[PDB]
Image (cartoon, rainbow, N blue to C red; front, top):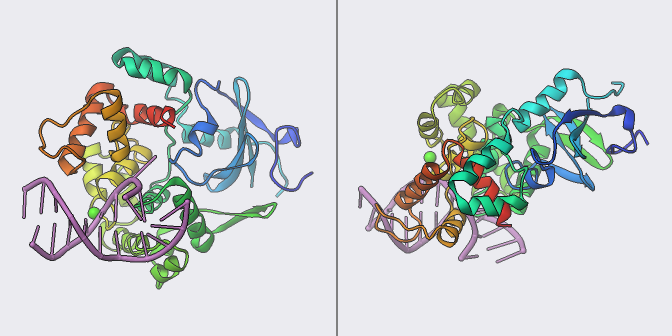
Length: 312
DNA sequence: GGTAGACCTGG
DNA sequence: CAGGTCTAC
Ligand SMILES: [Ca+2]
């Protein structure tokens, strides 16, 4: 009973809650949607993963978000630990208000988003986010999730073990920048991405100023932030936009891939004006990204998540 | 200065 | 061929 992953019903006394109706957050819509790849629904409707360097299990009901953390001597989440969960889901950002704004300026959203409330962006760590998305090249959520999982098992610090699952924190810069890491990563199937992880871990640490550099980008402007990241090997416009949108607090960033194009040509009859190329291209993509930022406003990136979900 | 191609591996 | 990046035309 005191073993394995917990459930709200099995170990009641060890849970705490955060007021949050499903209209504000839908775990099943956000945790496996491809923002973070470290959450698993071990028990139905129960998600487990590493948040703030500790293992948590989250599950929601009516107007509550239930949290339980595995640090000894158990005990429900504390006032502050639960606060970390709040910052992670950026709950202070009200979706009810955003859906209202986007819906009032975009009829197609109005309809489409009705059946998909509770979609929002996670406030991730710049490192985990930088390296996870460097691995998303020529890949899908399932592939990426696997790679990222073996990567932490191999170089991340061992947290705690639940059932036959051992949790690891995301690798540090020192670890990814170490000797022979690229070779190690290739054995884990990362392919050519192995080079970028390693090259990028070294660049931040030996050419840019380390962790601080990355972090400091949360205070910089979207344009500065975007430019900075692109400096890294394996980090282009797309990955830079994801990192900006997902870890550096830039809600206006709008990552453009052939997917966003499909949603644009099918639900808006969008077409490139400036750039000549009709298919995706550096210039046409930038243009497409500007279209949505003009259409949805500052949180264009959050609106995109909503559509991607409903398009599933 | 904008556009094919290789880089790993597997569904 | 794939939710990308890098580089030689
Ligand atoms: Ca780059």
